[PDB]
Length: 155
Image (cartoon, rainbow, N blue to C red; front, side, top):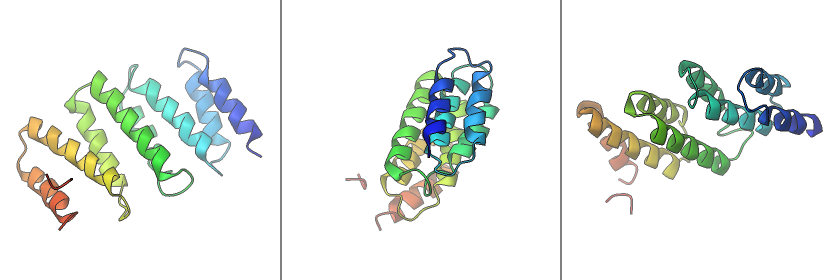
């Protein structure tokens, strides 16, 4: 059933250069997201190239496309590990001035009551970025959410 999508994802995975490869990953996505795990992996690679080389708003758009397979299609664990690894790559590469907005969009899309560590660790690291930003107003709202999540992590 998924025999085609696996091959097109594996074919677009090579190429080395992002030229014509991003459009091939877009073709993998265009083969409709019925599963759609392979579209998630295609976008994950598209993200992996986009913030590493040139343009950033396109990465924000494709990341917003990634934030749809959280509850449906792909499991919570694989999406959590993918988001965590991507956030670590951006944190090592670029600084707060881009990273903070991606953290904000991640928390804006994770509107789910079952998110325990998924909401917490992202809100905590955003709190650290807000501490580096010298913002204390919205940081109190972040700390209000974090304190109300309990009323290990409390410390």
